[PDB]
Image 1 (spheres, each protein chain N blue to C red):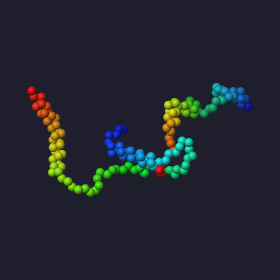
Image 2: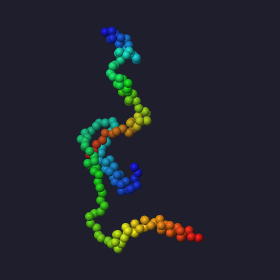
Image 3: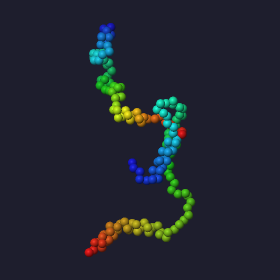
Length: 94
Length: 60
């Protein structure tokens, strides 16, 4: 697996930091203190779906109407090869 | 008695006779010993020495 997203990089790093903070690790030599184990760690470091926005925000408008954007994006993508063909065939003139 | 005398004759030795080797089973003769399964290459010996499974817990 390879990381190409920084929020996830940071979150996993944060989990590791919490874990290293949250454990105590015995020596190899011993003296074996009383540990009083936990049955699971998924409970204490639960997978946590993150926030995307607080409930409240102000409105702003842009006059694009949010449907024409999608429509002409569709149009540009489906006619990209032909517009490139037009550009190239006028470019290679003389 | 003759068996015990022969054991004391063949004592402390390798290749003692067939009806005084153990009988256990065909498979549990034709198979690996304690030492021979504990035999393991020096690479993984170093591995298990340097990075062994540590005894940890979670409160803090």
